[PDB]
Image (cartoon, rainbow, N blue to C red):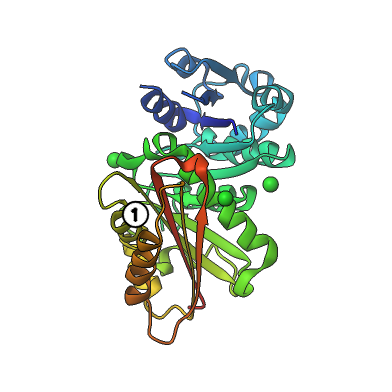
Amino acid sequence: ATLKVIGVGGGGNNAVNRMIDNNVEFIAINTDGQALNLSKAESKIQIGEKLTRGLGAGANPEIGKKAAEESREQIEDAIQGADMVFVTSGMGGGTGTGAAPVVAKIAKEMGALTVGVVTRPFSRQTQAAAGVEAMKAAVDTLIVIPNDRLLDIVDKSTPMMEAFKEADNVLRQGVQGISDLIAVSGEVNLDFADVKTIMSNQGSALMGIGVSSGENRAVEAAKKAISSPLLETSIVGAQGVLMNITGGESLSLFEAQEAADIVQDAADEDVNMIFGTVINPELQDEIVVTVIATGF
Ligand SMILES: [Cl-]
Ligand SMILES: [Cl-]
Ligand SMILES: [Cl-]
């Protein structure tokens, strides 16, 4: 499975520059031609050249949205061949904010599992909130992750793709009535209220993702999956919890039972829990635990 990481706008370009420093391709997209010159990505696309001709360096999301639509054909050609796509506009609230949803819409309408990666903190009248809402509408799964843990999505790409495929199958079948899902990785400083606005009023779920390898991998992966402030409060009171651990041939029943215990003890006593264990060679020595909390 081939992955493509697309940084949109100044923020995404800087994110992409850091992640370059494999089997993952990097694309940089921006309305600002001056900034793409500073991108280290092998694939660069300047979008909306007709639309932005004569303008200066602007911060209008609408220009970015229409810039991406003007260059739709160039974007499809660069994404062609991608199984999964990571789209992020990074720490910026300008054109990239508007272009990034369109890039995801293209990746999605091309049949690639499309993940929106949000590093910019948010919660309502900021441009950040508007962008996050727009991205949410366009992607299969939105994932919120600390800016300093950004390299994890490329470093641990194969386990992450298993987690996003799990979220995809949960949505498709409406497991435990879930119809809307946001993913979390790392020490994301948020509570359900900060994201309640932009999720469906019934069927909303939060998925924590923990990945680890080496010694005490199962314990660490399971604890990271529930260590985010967002999962710590949501897991308490959660009427339902979907728990899955996936590893390679080396995954023992001891590691699987321990991970389940850690999640069960954190969860409510009356919680309706579904436990899953999967032996998947492709993970090699990596472990990934997903914990989906619903029914708040
Ligand atoms: Cl899809
Ligand atoms: Cl930061
Ligand atoms: Cl699998």
Of residues 88 and 207, the one nearer the viewer is 207
Of residues 85 and 10, the one nearer the viewer is 85
| x 49%, y 23%: residue | 57
Total of numbered circles in the picture? 1
Position of 144 with respect to 74 (left or right) is: left
Which residue appears farthest toward the top when viewing the image? 37
Q: Looking at the rendering, in which quadrant would you find the N terminus? A: top right
| x 29%, y 55%: residue | 220
Determine whether 171 is above or below 77 in the image: below
Determine whether 294 is above or below 278 in the image: below
**Residue 110: x and y, percent?**
73, 37
| x 46%, y 12%: residue | 37
| x 57%, y 47%: residue | 135
Which residue appears farthest toward the left when viewing the image? 215
**Quarter of image, ligand 2:** top left
Determine whether 104 is above or below 193 in the image: above
Determine whether 74 is above or below 271 in the image: above
Residue 74: image quadrant is top right
Disc 1 crowd rating (10 Å Cα; few below 14, some 14-19, many 20+) is many
Residue that label 1 marks = 221
Position of 84 with respect to 117 (left or right) is: right
Of residues 194 and 234, the one nearer the viewer is 234
**Residue 170: x and y, percent?**
61, 62
Residue 79: image quadrant is top right
**Residue 99: x and y, percent?**
59, 35
At label 1, which amino acid type do we have? Ala
Which residue appears farthest toward the bottom when viewing the image? 270
- Is the shortest distance between ligand 3 and the CB of mark 1 under 8 Å? no
Position of 267 with respect to 294 (left or right) is: left
**Residue 145: x and y, percent?**
39, 48
As helix, strand or loop, the secondary structure at mark 1 comes to helix
